Image (tube, rainbow, N blue to C red):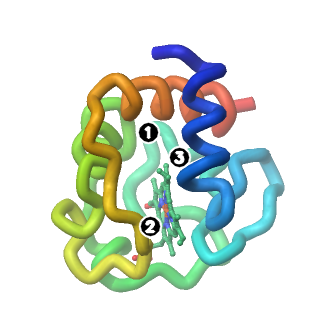
Amino acid sequence: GDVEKGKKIFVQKCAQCHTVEKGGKHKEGPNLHGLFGRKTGQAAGFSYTDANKNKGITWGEDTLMEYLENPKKYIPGTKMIFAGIKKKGERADLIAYLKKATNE
Ligand code: HEC
């Protein structure tokens, strides 16, 4: 995916609730640094719902593609309030951004 486009998508749709950098603050949602290859509900120091803690999947390209299409369908009872991104390209770009930004 296109990392620059993904950043713009992140800023538009995600950044008000999430930081990405190492040591970034939790906000309404958790800081996302280190997400890739991590199980659900494992950012330190954040009160997740039991639903997000209990989902039990490993975050990566395949599971983010599904989740981001419709978060509440993938994790029913999540307190993340975001309807989803319908477009496959847009999700791929966003994921490519996340794979860089969350690992820097
Ligand atoms: C606030 C209004 C949010 C917006 C907009 C987005 N997210 Fe979010 N996210 C938010 C909360 C409160 C939580 C925790 C949910 C729970 O039920 O405890 C989350 C969680 C996620 C996660 C899972 C993190 C993990 O398992 O460690 C991911 C991967 C995630 N959020 C990503 C994400 C992206 C990419 C968004 C824009 C498309 C986005 N979120 C929007 C709150 C909010």
* The residue at label 2 has a CB less than 8 Å from ligand 1: yes
Q: Which disc is residue 104 wearing?
A: none
Residue 85 image offset from top left, x and y in percent:
33, 46
Residue 51 image offset from top left, x and y in percent:
29, 79
Q: Please tell me which residue is depicted at 41% across the width and 81% down the height of the picture.
A: 79
Q: In the picture, residue 54 is in which quadrant?
A: bottom left
Q: Counting other residues with Cα less than 10 Å from the Cα at mark 1, is it few (<14), some (14-19), or many (20 or more)?
A: few
Question: What is the spatial separation of the Cα atoms under label 2 and label 3, in whole angstroms?
Answer: 10 Å
Residue 32 placement, left or right of 93 = right
Residue 15 image offset from top left, x and y in percent:
66, 55
Q: Please tell me which residue is depicted at 24% across the width and 56% down the height of the picture.
A: 70
Label 3 SS:
loop
Q: Counting other residues with Cα less than 10 Å from the Cα at mark 3, is it few (<14), some (14-19), or many (20 or more)?
A: many
Disc 2 marks a residue whose amino acid type is Gly
Is 91 or 50 nearer to us in this picture? 91
Residue 92 image offset from top left, x and y in percent:
39, 26
* Residue bearing the label numbered 2: 41
Q: Which disc is residue 37 wearing?
A: 1
Question: What is the spatial separation of the Cα atoms under label 1 and label 3, in whole angstroms?
Answer: 6 Å
Q: Please tell me which residue is depicted at 43% across the width and 73% down the height of the picture.
A: 80
Is the residue 18 above or below the residue 85 in the image?
below
Q: Which disc is residue 35 wearing?
A: 3
* The residue at label 3 has a CB less than 8 Å from ligand 1: yes
Question: What is the spatial separation of the Cα atoms under label 2 and label 1, in whole angstroms?
Answer: 12 Å
Residue 24 placement, left or right of 90 = right
